[PDB]
Each structure stands twice: as structure tokens, then as C-alpha cells.
């Protein structure tokens, strides 16, 4: 359905990306609208002096690619004058930049010619007409990929921006598996960037990284499709796929992973007290909805009436969809009025929808969770499975039983 | 290409959006790229509104260009008419749609929708969100407000209040109470409480009350020319400005002043010996020009503060800002850049800062007591409690809010010395 | 003997002084040693009263002991009558005057003052400030309130509000607006804004509303027995409690239950997604029993908080305190030692603390979000702005006040994470 | 002269004394009235766990003198177990403790016997039946004096409790002048208690240490009668009088005190712009009124109309009274109603009164400045002379600004 879509442009991906890449500054070439969106979705981070700025396109900047590119070079040089700490610059494309047809790929090359050893300028497009929400993150990662050095050693490879605690616990469990040194593409600094080659088979931690998956396939790396680490079972099958690819014995794997699986099961059971026998609706927000529905329906016992995804990458999400029950209705494309009528008719007990839609549905009487929190808060692996379960346990439906 | 991290004002379409969500029956059909619906979150969370903003977006992509994008615009306006069923439709375009060559007005006429349709040509790159709200309100008034018979009893229009405005709801309530105590009813509150019918009735009011010039001055100057409705030049923030407002409203209406002082407490709690230490405390002020000009008078003439910094981010009110700051022996800081106000605060090193939310965070990093007085705010700066900044109860709220940081700093220092 | 550093309640004569200060035309000639004039600073500073407390002190010294004390008291009463010309006199004793054997009431009667003289028998060493206020209000009612023909229209009495009371001034206004919205006029508010003439007309009310049992339960019961006036058992703090109070007051008056929820925003703002993190926040509650019970009901029913602590310092309300605490599954902490409250908080580690200023200072050293709900407060806690704790506007104020510490803590925590 | 006395018992000075002596606890044997006064006057101090507490009496305590003494003994034992850092316990009297005839002298001797020498238990009275405000500090110092060790040295005793910065300025200026040993009677710790002998000579800093003056005179100490160190001239004359007793000549005095005098005069002139040509009314709170009305009259140019003090010690305030102009009338008898009538009749430009009287006078239309701040804030010597002037200036500045 082609209608109004209440989803974020991919410049929102910058907001959580720069927290993982402490060496990278993201410069957005956009209008006042893009800067306003970036600051609104950042919230307090913009008060915390973060590493994203918007080179605002002025009226004189609209006419003339050479003039606008010269002013862009001026601003970039001024920024590295202020910020010699950062070595990575991302010339994030934006909707007005695309309409101007201001080539930012060329600009990245020119700035790399200027101060390449000092700063490595990458380039991707977070524009709304091109990219939606976490597609900004995966576009940034896919931009990073081609420049990455080649390696000739088979190493375990992790793709996706994760909190440092989640990344540490993930690599910890991968190490207790015993086989396969780990590496993460969104490296905190460009110095510790990974080497990507045909031998390094890569595992994707977050579903929406489809462009990054394609870019890694161009490098020769093959993908091990697996259900993403949301909850105990998804994390278990993710680690099991990784272990099978690296030939870890089944009994050894079960023995090493039993304790965190038991803790995650206890935590999800404790959190999912009011979740059993409940109906959950998903609006297209963050491409996490398929794995979200899998986790909720299986571990939490919450039947999914409709799973809405802005872009469904069937090839990578195949194991997760296989884990998902036949009952949930996966839908592609977003018409906000059609999906609003659908949630109104279905009368879901919980609706995981956008923040611009969350409060209206609460006013109408629908319990709503906003999925924008999910990309922020740690919701991956066992140690956060309980928090992930409780996040849907009380986005009301624990407050509804308290307010009403 | 100036590198911007914080903007004090959004794009003009955001202000027009505030005007749209203020009224009922007015839908903003915005020509915008997919992902420009972020500002709905502002209304649903910042202001905590029960209903979705009356905004319909085209949300075009790269596959839809030329004939397609115009077709999506047609579909968006038609769908808005069919399912939202508003009494009036107002059509605008975002920055990206401003660049692309699609005439917002022409397609609306092509639809020939029965409801009145206003087209707002808002320069996205030249102008900002306050101009967007002002020009949107002006266009709405031009299309719907017409000369009409005056009301039998004296009535006024509260011009300026919009959604996402700072303390606009409680200020509406307080000024309404002040006028009913004065014998003047409120004909309409536009656009925060108005509708196409109410915008039509705007011409029935004897005079307008320009509550917020930032968003209402264009409509006031148009209604002073087409509807022959003079508007009050004084904004009633603080005791002195409240008395000035009461005097001008009595003069315009012809009624007796009749100001209700019985609940006033700002004068005494400022004259009490507990407020003696307030004397000579230096205050820095920034924000929209109206609030800064009013708050400087409150801080000096009513609280014993000395104003060391006086500025506005709203360059539209540059002459009034500078003229006000000249009366305090200062040069007005008319800047849209927060690093400039940061430099001003660091140079002046005030004892209290009264400004927007970025001003508050600058103070918190610098360890200076801070209170919020201006439009750019958070969800936390929209109280559930009655918190007017205008009128006599607004004076009490002002005193408490401006004194709380100083009281909390004094108490913390005393505890630090004691322990 | 016990070493006390902080007292939740003062001596009974302080409560009697509160009753005298709230009332007009009422004077308290207190037999006190020189230097017991200290509690006048409480009323002049904490409440910012522009008029000195209507209390006359004998201020006897070592030289004035034995025979001289009675003559000093008699001269004090007669001179207070000559100077202030009050319409009724309270005579009372301090701890020191209780220790010495002067009969205050006998001396006052021997003077034969024209105006009614109220004898105050407040055991100072075994009782406290709230007993002093309650007993003083009692004896004033017994001396002056008499069976009187009821008003032709339905009328009510607001009983309980005494000076130096936590937001008594704004609660009076809120309950008055509630009753007027019902159609019930307030015959008299006492002790605040009362006179001996008003205590005379206290018998003209159809029923009594006991806003504050701590300072008015004895008077309400006395009116029930003699004046045949039933009193409300529901304190309208919080939406649920306000609606129960609405129903009860309508039943007592005989009018249909009508309340204005238009300005009420607490339910929606707690139902909003922004308030979702409030679910399950453990709260400790301490202070005066009425406020603690009301705040516990508000927290659990309307805020999503789980009450993990509940207590009061009024042993006069221990049975209601324990009965209320059983509803939440805990044992009430009925104590007057701040060390016991600190021990309970430390062993309990609440996420939010709602209580007195002592509890607002225990939280800071433990780094716990805190807010003030009960009577022991500072000058800062008495606000210039309209800050009721009763009614629907009081519910909005409660929401904002209780959420402000949590919002601040979350914002500072996020700032620390973002570095 | 006799009537309602709007003052504080001397239990208020305990708040300053616990700040100035860090090893001293002030146990108050009083009722809930005295505990409530202590917490109300402390304000924020009670939330910092101060070193003063009230042993609130019960009915059984009034009935049984022996029972009350035993319970007080148990309370003192529990106190010292709880706070071993205390080295000197101050059993302060109160109005009830006097009426019950609870002899705190016997309790002090007994507890000094059993808890000696780790904690020294002195007895003084803060009862408002006997004392008033700063007379509590005077009683504490006069109770300290008899237990001081005897010395044969020529030592200067800086009698009076001062803020640490003010005391540091005092000792620095004195050492620069050329005097010998300087000790302070309100010592920070019990180990630093000075010695008093026939050769000991002491100088009063605050104009209310009359009983301390008498107690030191009984031990053989001699008073350096000087104008109290308030403002530039007051500090100058104080140091000059100490110098005349110590042999410091005019040359060294002017080579040492010229710079602080010169800067203090400028500070006072800058901070007393609105005070010049304005009348000031003093009501009896802290006995600071004459020695500070002298500063206001001479330096700030104020025209004092009436100076009210709880009681004059003309012996120790003699020089400062001499520097007073003949114009102001001075009152030692306090009837708050008659004094308020006098204030109304005079219509002063400034009215130094108590905290209880401040707000009503402000509502009547008189600018007021509470004298409690004067005792709490540092307003002594040279550096704070400008602060002293600004304390009285800011009420007038606020009144001019707000109108
Ligand atoms: S990138 Fe496009 S959709 Fe996103 S904020 Fe900028 S203009 Fe709007
Ligand atoms: S005057 Fe006496 S009873 Fe009153 S507080 Fe002082 S010592 Fe206690
Ligand atoms: Cu706070
Ligand atoms: Cu705060």
C-alpha cells in the first residue's frame, strides 16, 4: 500500500551510530528540516555536544555544485580545525542534497585527497526518499565496507552497532564457544577496523542490515542466516548456527550455554507475567518487527496479529520467519491510515508503533510500545532478554491494569 | 553550509504545523519526503496531545518524480478530504518539495475541493518556524476571516497562541480570567483554540489581543487593516506589564480597568526580607524576543536583578530587541547560533540565566542557576499543573520558577559549608 | 529522656499559635519565658506574613518568679486587649509556665475582659503541636459556636486549615471552587480566614468538610454532637479521593455530584507513553497521616508506583495509619524519630521519597529522588504560585511535583551517559 | 521598659559555638519548645547533623530529680559512645531545667568525674529566663574560663568566637604588627585551650562578652578596652589599643595597617552609597547595636535615631560609646510594643530588628535588616567592612529598585 508512511528518514541512524563509533563524525548536508529532525530525535545528546552536524543548505548553496562543494570543503576543514580527535567523516546524503544532485561521493574523494592520512571521509545517503530509519545505520556500514582491508584468515565477523555491554557479552559467549575470533565492522576507531575477506564468514546481529550484508557478499564473505539474538531462543539459535559453522560440538555448546539460557528464560518468564495470551500489533518502524514477533509469540506467549515491516529482506530473515508461527500476518509497505484501521479493528492488547502514533492510540484505548526505544536500549542476547521482555511487559498492560 | 547542531527554530513548515494542530477542522496536507513526519512526534510527546496532528504527508520517494509526485500530492489532499473530513484544508511543502518543481497551490485548485484551501508559500531556507507559524496564521485569516458585524458585548481575540508554544494553554486561561474580570469576553482564541468557523468569527471581535507577536503579529496587522481591529502592543508578563495590559485593554474596550490583585503575591514575596539577597544578582536572558523583553522588565523592575545579557534568537524582532536592550545599557544579542550565546554567557558570567532549554543546559554545564522562560522546551517544560507565565498568577509562577534555582543553589552551598 | 535534634511537631502552644494566626480578631496571650517569642519568626518568615502573629507574651525572667508571674500575665492580657482590641482572647501556658503554678485561666477570668476568653489546657510535655491546634480550635468552638438556624441555601464549613499548614491556602481555594461548582456555598473557613463572629455562625452550616483532621477532627466531632453537623471522612487529595469526596459531599448536601474535570490532566498524562517508566517505581511515604494516606492512594492508583514504605509522625492517627498501610501490605512506621525513618529508607532503598523536609534531606544524602508532601517544610516550600494538593488542579500539581525529581534524575543520568 | 521582649534565649548562640568548636557538643536539657527553637534557628544546620541536641524532658523527668539525673547520665553515656570525637560536652541549662531546679553543676561534676579526662563536662545556662541570644555565647565562654590552666607568660587572649577567615585575618594582622602570642579562648579543640595568668592580657572582639570579661578578670587577666573591630576605623582603633599595650609604635603600625585601612575605606564607601544621609533604628537583639551603630554613623554617614540593646555593658563598650555621636538616644529596656511605636513615630530609613519583627515592619513601609545575619555573617575587621556596609545597603537598594 502506497500511502502516508510514519517512519523516520535514515538520518536517525546517525543518532545511535556515533555512540558506537567514537572516532567518526557524521556531517549531514541538508536543510533546516534535517537538522531539526536530527536534534529532535537526539534529545539530550545534542545538549551533550555530539558528533553529528548539519551543513545547512542555504539559498545561495542551492545553485551551483562547485560553489556549494567549496563551502562544504570550507566547513569540513573548519570542523577538523575544531575536531582533530576524529579520523572518520561521513558526508551523509539528505533529501535536499539528493534533489540538488550534489555529488557527495566525489566530495569524499576530494577530502580524502586533501587530508586522507589525517581523516578518512566515507559517504552514504541517509535521505528519506532513499533510506528509512535503521537503513541509515546499514547504509553507513555498507559505505564503510568497500574501503575495509582484505584478509586471508577465516575469522568470526559481527555486523551491527551494539552497546558496549552487549558487544562484550556477545564476544564473551563466542569465546566460551572456543572457535572463531570475533570482529565488529562498526569499530569504535578506524585504527581497529576489521579485515574482510572471502574466508571471514559474517554473522549479522540486527535484521535491518541488508545493504551491509550485500556489501559483505561483494567482498566474497558468505552469510550464515540465523535467527537474531532477541530473547533466549533467538540468541540460542544464533549461537548454535555460529557454532555449527565453526564445528563446535553440540554437547559442549549446550553445556557452556546452559546457564545464561536458564537465566534468560527465568527473566523472560518473570517479565512476561501479563504478556501470556495477549495480542500484539506491529507498525513498520525499525525492521525489527519479524524477530520481535518471533520472540514475543514464542517466549512471551503473545500472539502476533500483524507484523508490519517497512522493508522485509526475506533472504536474511528466513530462519526467523521459519521460527515465526503461521498466524502472524507479515505485511510490506506502509499506509498509515490503512494500518491504523487494521489496529483499530484487530483490537490488539499491545501495539508496537511509532512515537508519533503511540500517544494517539493510547488515547483511543490501545496499549502502545514505541519501537524507537528498542534500537536505543540493549535488547539483545540473554543478559538483556529479561529487559527486552519487560519492555513489552509494561508499556502499559501493566499500567493499564494499574490505571484502569 | 554553516555546521548546525542546534536550531532554535524549526523549518517554517513546523510552525505552520503548529498552527494546524492548534485549530480543529484545519488539516495540513504537506508535500514532504518520507521521513519528514518526525514533527508529529513533537506534538504527540512534547505537548502530550491525545489526537494525531492534523497533518497529512505525501512521503514521496525517489521512484516517484515528475508526474508521479504531483499525483501523490493530489491523492494526499483528496484522501484528507475523504477520510479526515476537515472544514478547511491548508497545503504546504517541505524543503525537499520546495526544491522540486511542484506547484502546491495549482493542484489544490485542480481538485476543486469544496472546503476552502489556503496555500502557504514559506521560504524554507530563508525563513524559520516562527515565520512559518505567523505566515500560516496570516494566510488562514486572509482566506477565512472576513469583515462582519461587531459583537453586542465587548469581545477580544487572543491572537498568537499555538500548539508547542511555551505556556500557551495556561496563559490563555489566565488572560481569559483577567479579561472576564474586566468585563470583556473572549470572542475567539486563535489558532490554538480556533476553527475555520472561529477564524471566520475573528472579525466580530471589537479588538485583538496580541498575546504572542512572534506568531500573531502578521495576523494582527492584517486585522488592523481589513477588520479594523486594534491590537494590544503590550504582552502581560509580570506585574507591571500586566497593569499596562489592563490599562490598554480598558482603553480599547472602554470598560473600567478592574484588575484582580487579591491573589497577587509577587510584590510581597519579593519585598520580603527573604528576597533581599536577590538584589544585584546578574541575569542573562535569551529566547524569543517577546519573552526576553518581558522577562528583563520583570527581573529588573520587580525582582531587583541587574540584566547583564539581553538577546533573542528571533531575528524578526531585531528592532524591538535592540530597543529594549538599549534601555538596560546593553547591546542586544540577536543571534540564531547557540555558540554565540555560550560565548556571551562565558564572558558575562551571570549569577542566573533565564532562557530556552539550550540556555538551561549551558548553565548546567557552567554551574549557573537556570530557569526556562522561552519557547524551545522539552516534554518536562509542559506542566500538567496550571503554570501561566502571563497575568497576575503568571507573576507568581514567574517568581517561584526564577527563584527556585537561586534557593536551591543557596541551600546547597549552605549544606556544603555545614557538612 | 531522649536526645532529639529534629522534631516533626513543635510544642502544643505552637499549634495554638497557628490557630490564633490563621484566625482574625483572635489573640493568644501566652504565658511564656523571655525568649519564647521565637515562633513568630515561623509565621513571618516561612509563610511570609505581613502582620505580626497576634500573640502576646509575658516573657517573664528569673526576677519575675513566684508572685510576680501572675501579675505579669494579668498585665500582659489586659495590655494586649487595650492595644490590639481583639474580639476574643486565648490564654495559655508554655512548658515553663506549665511547670510553675500560675493558673492562666483563673487570672484571665479575674481580669474580667469584655471579650470571650478561651482557656487553653495543653499538656506540653506529653502532647505536641497538632494536639495544641486541635484542642485550641475545639475550645474556641465550644466557647463561641452555638446551635444556630441553618442557612436557607445549602452551605458548608471548611474545617481544619490552620496557619503554617502545608498548602492550606491553595487547598481552601480549590475546595471552595469544587463546592461552588456543585452549588454549595462555604459558610465559613476555620481557623484560617475565620473570626469569633464566624465561629458564632459555624452552627449555620448544613454540614462540615474536614479538610485537615489533624487540626480539626475534634471540632468536627463536637459540631456533630452539639451543632448536628456531619463531617466528611474523605480528604480530596488525588483524582480518586477527589471524586469520592465529590460523591460524599453531594450526598451530604443533597445536590447532584458535579465536578469539573476539564482542567484535569493527571489521568491522561499518566496514561501517556512518557509516564510508562513510572510503572513499578518503589516509593517511601512519610509525614502527617492524612497526607501520607492520600499520597499512597494517589501513587498506587494513579501513578503506577508500588508503595514500599508508609508512615506518619502523628500517634493520634496511628490506627488510621496502620489500617491504610494494611491495604498496601505493609506495616505503618508510626514514629517521631527521624533516625527511624532514615533506617527504614536505607533498609528499603526507595526509588522515590515523598515526605517532609526531613525526608527531603535524607533522600539527598542517599541520592534518592525526593518531593515534599507533608507539613514540616521550609520557607521555600510555601509557594507564591497557586499550589494546591487537593482537587483536580491539586492532582495536576501532585503529578508535576512528584515527577520532577524522577525527570531530573533521568535527565542528569542521560547527560552523564552521553558525557 | 518591662513587657514583651522579642528576643531569643541564649540557646541560639549554641549554633555559632558548635561551628567554632569542633570537639564540643552542646546538650540542651530543655523541653520540646527549646528543641523546636534550636531547629528553627539552625534552619539548614540541623540537616547536616550538627553537634547540638536537646534532651527533651518528660513528666517523669520533672517529677523525679534523681530519676532525671540518672536519665541524663545515661543519655550522656550514650552520646559519648555514639560520638567519640567529642572532647568537651556542654550541659547547657534551659528554662524548664531551671524551674525543675535540675542542678546541671552537679551533673557536670559527676560526668567529668566518670568520663574524665576524655570528655570535659562544663555547665552554662542558655535559659531565656536568665540569658538572651549572644548571652549564650557569653555564658559558654564564662563557663570555659575557670577551668583554663594557669600560665606565667605574657599572652594575648583574643576573646570572642569569630568566623575562621575573620580569625585568620585577625592573627595575620596582629603578627604583622609585632605582638607576642595570640590565643583564642573559644579554641577549636580542647588541647588548644589557652592559659590565663596575672600577666595575661585579653581583648574583646564582640560587644557582649561581659560575663567572660568578669570571669577573665577574676583570674587576673586585664582588658584591652578598645572599639570593637567593626569597619575600617573600628578595626584601626582596636589594633591601636592592642598595640599601645604591646609597645607597637606608630611607624610600624602605619607600615602594616595602611594598606588594609586604605582598601577597607574604599570598600565601605563603595558599599555604603545609599546609606549616607539616612537614619537607622536599632532594636535590642544581639548587643552589637552600639558598636555597629558607631560604624554606621561615622563611616557610612548614617544618622542613628535610636540604638536599642538587650543590656549595656558600659565598661566594655566604653570606647565605642565614646565614639558615638550625642544625637542618637540609647535604650536598654525592651518592650516590643513601645519600641515598635517608637519606630513608627521615627519613620526610620533603615530598621535593624529581629527576624520576627522584620516582615511586619516591611509591610508597614519600613526598610529592615535582621541583626541575626550580623552574628552569623563575617562582618568584622577589614576585608569584611565592605560586606558589613553592603549588608545594610542592600535593603535600601532593594527598596529603591522595587519602587
Ligand atoms: S533527510 Fe529528507 S526526510 Fe529526513 S529530515 Fe532531511 S529532508 Fe526530512
Ligand atoms: S526561652 Fe526557655 S523554654 Fe523557650 S526555647 Fe529558650 S530555653 Fe527553651
Ligand atoms: Cu530539584
Ligand atoms: Cu530542580
Image (cartoon, coloured by chain):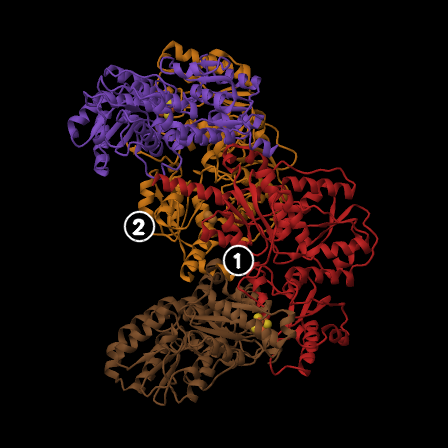
Chain colours: A purple, B orange, C red, D brown
Q: Quadrant of residue C418?
A: top left
For residue C366, above or below residue D185: above
CA distance for labels 1 and 2? 47 Å
- Per the image, label 1 sits on a secondary structure element best described as helix
Residue C90 point in image, percent of width and height: 71, 67
Q: Chain of mark 1?
A: C
For residue A243, above or below residue B374: above
* Residue at left offset 49%, top offset 20%: A297
- Per the image, label 2 sits on a secondary structure element best described as helix
User: Which residue is label 2 attached to?
Assistant: B347
Residue D57 point in image, percent of width and height: 60, 70
Q: Nearer the viewer, residue B35 or A316?
A: A316
Is residue D272 visible to us here? no
Q: Nearer the viewer, residue D10 or B299?
A: D10
Relative to B43, is D32 on the left or the right?
A: right
User: Which residue is label 1 attached to?
Assistant: C339
Residue C397 point in image, percent of width and height: 57, 44
The local crowd at label 1, few if under 14, some if 14 to 19, many if 20 or more residues have their Cα within 10 Å, is: some
Q: Residue furthest top?
A: B67
* Residue at left offset 68%, top offset 50%: C320
Amino acid at each position: 500500500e502506497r500511502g502516508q508512511r510514519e517512519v523516520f528518514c535514515g538520518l536517525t541512524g546517525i543518532i545511535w551510530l556515533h555512540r558506537k563509533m567514537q572516532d567518526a563524525f557524521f556531517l549531514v548536508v541538508g536543510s533546516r528540516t534535517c537538522a531539526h529532525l536530527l536534534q529532535s530525535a537526539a534529545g539530550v545528546m545534542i545538549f551533550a555536544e555530539p558528533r553529528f552536524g548539519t551543513a545547512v543548505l542555504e539559498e545561495k548553496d542551492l545553485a551551483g555544485l562547485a560553489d556549494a562543494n567549496a563551502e562544504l570543503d570550507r566547513e569540513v576543514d573548519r570542523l577538523l580545525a575544531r575536531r582533530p580527535d576524529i579520523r572518520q567523516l561521513f558526508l551523509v546524503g539528505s533529501c535536499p542534497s539528493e534533489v540538488i544532485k550534489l555529488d557527495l561521493h566525489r566530495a569524499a574523494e576530494r577530502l580524502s585527497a586533501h587530508h586522507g592520512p589525517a581523516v578518512r571521509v566515507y559517504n552514504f545517503s541517509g535521505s528519506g526518499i532513499e533510506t528509512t530509519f535503521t537503513q541509515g545505520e546499514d547504509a553507513c556500514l555498507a559505505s564503510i565496507v568497500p574501503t575495509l582491508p582484505a584478509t586471508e584468515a577465516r575469522e568470526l565477523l559481527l555486523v551491527g552497532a551494539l552497546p558496549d555491554v552487549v558487544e562484550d557479552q556477545a564476544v564473551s559467549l563466542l569465546t566460551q564457544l572456543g572457535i572463531g575470533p570475533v570482529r565488529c565492522l562498526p569499530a569504535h576507531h578506524a585504527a581497529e577496523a576489521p579485515g574482510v575477506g572471502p574466508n571471514t564468514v559474517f554473522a549479522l546481529v540486527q535484521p535491518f542490515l541488508g545493504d551491509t550484508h550485500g556489501a559483505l557478499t561483494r567482498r566474497g564473505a558468505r552469510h550464515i542466516a540465523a535467527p537474531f539474538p532477541f530473547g533466549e531462543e533467538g540468541t540460542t539459535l544464533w549461537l548454535k548456527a555460529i557454532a555449527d559453522e565453526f564445528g563446535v560440538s553440540a554437547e559442549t555448546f549446550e553445556a557452556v550455554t546452559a546457564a545464561p539460557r536458564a537465566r534468560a528464560r527465568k527473566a523472560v518468564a518473570a517479565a512476561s507475567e501479563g504478556l501470556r495470551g495477549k495480542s500484539v500489533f506491529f507498525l513498520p518502524d525499525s525492521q525489527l518487527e519479524p524477530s520481535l514477533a518471533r520472540f514475543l509469540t514464542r517466549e512471551c506467549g503473545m500472539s502476533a496479529v500483524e507484523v508490519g515491516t517497512p522493508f522485509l529482506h526475506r533472504g536474511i530473515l528466513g530462519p526467523d520467519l521459519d521460527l515465526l508461527a503461521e498466524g502472524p500476518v507479515l505485511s510490506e509497505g506502509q499506509d498509515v491510515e490503512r494500518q491504523l484501521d487494521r489496529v483499530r479493528a484487530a483490537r490488539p492488547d499491545l501495539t508496537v508503533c511509532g512515537l508519533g502514533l503511540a500517544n494517539p492510540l493510547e488515547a483511543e484505548g490501545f496499549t502502545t510500545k514505541w519501537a524507537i526505544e528498542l534500537v536505543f536500549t540493549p535488547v539483545h542476547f540473554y543478559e538483556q532478554a529479561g529487559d527486552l521482555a519487560g519492555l513489552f511487559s509494561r508499556p502499559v498492560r501493566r499500567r493499564a491494569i494499574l490505571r484502569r | 553550509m554553516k555546521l548546525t547542531l542546534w536550531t532554535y527554530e524549526g523549518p517554517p513548515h513546523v510552525g505552520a504545523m503548529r498552527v494546524a494542530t492548534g485549530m480543529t477542522g484545519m488539516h495540513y496536507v504537506l508535500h514532504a519526503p518520507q521521513g519528514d513526519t518526525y514533527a508529529d512526534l513533537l506534538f504527540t510527546m512534547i505537548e502530550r496531545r491525545g489526537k494525531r496532528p492534523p497533518v497529512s504527508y505525501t512521503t514521496f520517494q525517489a521512484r516517484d518524480l515528475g508526474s508521479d509526485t504531483a499525483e501523490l500530492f493530489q491523492s494526499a489532499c483528496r484522501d484528507a478530504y475523504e477520510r479526515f473530513q476537515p472544514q478547511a484544508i491548508m497545503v504546504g511543502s517541505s524543503c525537499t518539495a520546495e526544491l522540486i518543481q511542484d506547484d502546491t497551490g495549482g493542484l489544490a485548485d485542480a481538485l476543486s475541493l469544496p472546503v476552502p484551501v489556503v496555500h502557504l508559500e514559506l521560504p524554507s531556507y530563508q525563513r524559520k518556524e516562527n515565520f512559518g507559524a505567523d505566515e500560516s496564521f496570516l494566510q488562514i485569516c486572509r482566506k477565512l476571516a472576513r469583515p462582519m458585524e461587531r459583537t453586542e458585548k465587548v469581545s477580544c481575540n487572543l491572537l498568537g497562541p499555538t500548539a508547542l508554544g511555551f505556556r500557551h494553554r495556561d496563559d490563555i486561561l489566565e488572560v481569559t480570567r483577567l479579561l472576564e474580570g474586566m468585563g470583556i469576553a473572549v470572542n475567539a482564541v486563535a489558532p490554538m483554540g480556533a476553527s475555520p468557523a472561529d477564524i471566520a468569527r475573528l472579525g466580530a471581535a471589537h479588538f485583538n489581543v496580541l498575546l504572542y507577536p512572534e506568531t500573531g503579529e502578521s495576523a494582527a496587522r492584517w486585522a488592523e487593516k481589513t477588520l479594523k481591529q486594534p491590537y494590544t502592543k503590550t504582552v502581560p508578563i509580570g506585574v507591571g506589564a500586566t497593569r499596562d495590559f489592563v490599562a490598554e485593554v480598558a482603553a480599547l474596550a472602554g470598560v473600567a480597568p478592574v484588575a484582580d490583585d487579591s491573589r497577587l503575591r509577587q510584590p510581597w514575596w519579593s519585598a520580603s526580607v527573604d528576597s533581599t539577597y536577590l538584589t544585584g544578582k546578574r541575569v542573562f536572558l535569551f529566547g524569543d524576543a517577546t519573552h526576553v523583553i518581558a522577562a528583563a522588565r520583570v527581573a529588573r523592575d520587580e525582582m531587583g536583578f541587574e540584566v547583564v545579557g539581553m538577546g533573542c534568537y528571533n531575528r524578526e524582532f531585531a528592532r524591538p530587541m535592540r530597543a529594549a536592550a538599549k534601555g538596560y545599557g546593553l547591546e542586544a544579542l540577536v543571534t540564531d547560533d547557540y555558540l554565540e550565546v555560550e560565548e556571551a554567557i562565558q564572558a558575562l558570567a551571570p549569577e542566573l540565566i533565564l532562557g530556552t532549554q539550550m540556555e538551561r543546559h549551558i548553565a548546567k554545564r557552567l554551574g549557573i542557576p537556570c530557569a526556562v522562560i522561552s519557547a524551545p522546551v522539552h516534554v518536562q517544560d509542559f506542566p500538567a499543573r496550571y503554570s501561566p507565565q502571563m497575568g497576575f498568577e503568571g507573576a507568581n509562577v514567574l517568581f517561584d520558577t526564577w527563584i527556585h534555582p537561586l534557593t536551591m543553589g543557596l541551600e546547597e552551598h549552605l549544606l556544603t559549608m555545614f557538612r
